[PDB]
Length: 116
Length: 115
Length: 116
Length: 115
Image (cartoon, rainbow over all chains, first blue to last red; front, top):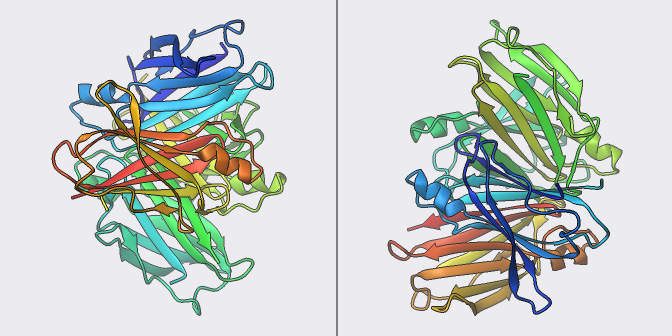
């Protein structure tokens, strides 16, 4: 509930199914520790990555495997992935939606942050 | 010089060449009267649409014929065109660049306004 | 259900509440006939604009009053509105989500089209 | 000449001036080794990062320090930075322009690749 990822294909106007997503948290050592992973559903959404308790203050990285998505459609895209890095929960708990809009040579990402 | 249009293709990663662009000025009776037009260059740009003398304050519309572009590439598009409607020079003349980034089912338009 | 509009503020990362939306349909005469209107909810969404029966083949125009939104926040934005023009239902009935992402000098719009 | 970065500010409608940009090359041990850096000009552009000789095939990362830009403007940002990771010249050398459009809670990056 605190962290959701949503992915859309701007060529077809359709959610992207089965796209891999990895989340990492920046370590006290400054390394990227694996934190959660999953794949998008038929709606293009990935829920259930974490809980309010586990999702503490930190720097988080959401890495979306956009290249495998395009390659499965026959396309050699520009980007290796889409990677979103942000500080979370530093003013207390929030709910974060990380959205990505994909084209072969472009991507856009927006964050919708709300207070529960 | 006061108005320029620059268009990019997010599918191919290239400027959009030979895209038609039409510019209109809102008339007093709230209709759109045609004002200038052209086709983007090989750099995706359209210069020379108007002059400082002619580009007075008012409401302007820029229409980019995105549907014809995508049809020429054999790609099904969503929109009939991409539009930008804006008020010009409300606080003095400026240079306006209308930058458009095109995908078949999405577009963004940004104004880069320099004094 | 066949037509939904969703609007987000890219400065704050938040849905835009109370934004006016007007829909028009291109006439047999080639005029823009008023078709439906409403305002976005606290989620930034506007539902219930039309029905499958009324929403026939045609060229439709969705006009979002982004300028009033910015002016209420003290900002003089570049665009007078955000206007999305598209052919609908020409290959049969579909569900359309028209999304807009707003900044004072920029907007993005994407269409998500699905088959029920 | 082979790599250029261009950055626009969607809030103010201007190029982003004095934004730091760092470029890295993936090393064989899968770490990022620093390769070039600079600050955007008054046109929002950063030229001269590398040369055709040095810009060989491989995986490159471009980091744009968007957070520092927004902090300088007194605007709260979401992201730590904007990134682009790409494979270069897989089918020959090309000119790459990485165009980034920035808002405090959203960004887009587009590659304009010309031969």
